[PDB]
Length: 109
Image (cartoon, rainbow, N blue to C red; front, side):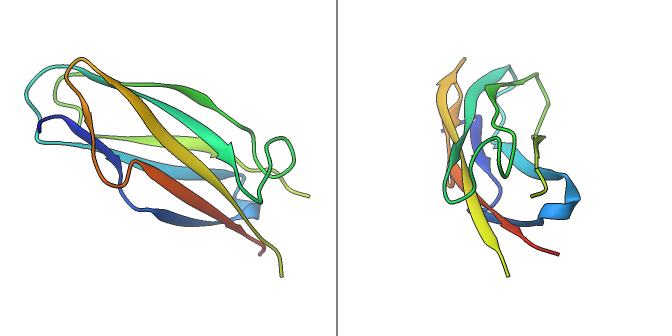
């Protein structure tokens, strides 16, 4: 498979006070053209509009592009909560690699 798109890790840890989770997505084995995948947050114990700002959209990789950083906003309110991000719907010859979902662990300062 070429143009394989994945999260770099299955889990990331962030402090709530950081205001943003910076989530890396990579594309490997580039064939030379564009690739697209969809992405979406999904609540776990962290909930949209309470713990973070939900987002969904498309990641369009132009020729040569090997990574992106998603930025999901974190909201301020011992405590640990998690939300998820999922890749789906590869287009233009893209494929999903492992891991194609990830968990963002929000910890207190």
